[PDB]
Image (cartoon, rainbow, N blue to C red; front, side, top):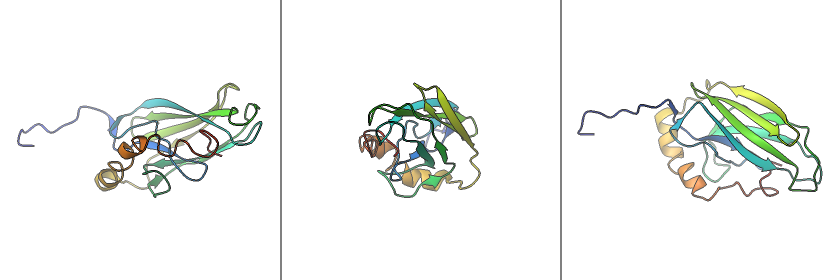
Length: 159
């Protein structure tokens, strides 16, 4: 501020990037001003007894959910391990590249089975205004909402 040295020596993306799920709500395993590239692993479960199939939708942003932050990507992952209700499960894995490019991989991990989307950050360009207004009340006050909308449909399920 008064001292002429206001600079951050880190390759960071401005927002905490997560996923819009079962009824359109978030889970953020990332963080605001995150030192990308980064591989995080959030284990979600399923709703029906023996083998659902998850429709994942990526939203960069959002206060305890269905506000309206930055939608990009989305994919359907299917081929689930059959166990009896709330126990069949999937790892929504987030492998981000250095220019804020999200390789989103849903893994049926006991089954060792993944499908992935590489999201290029071209449509939106939120920058200073959407990150200062949305993440100070969202990602900060969202894992502080207390895994906001993480306790969702059936335990941790995006169905």
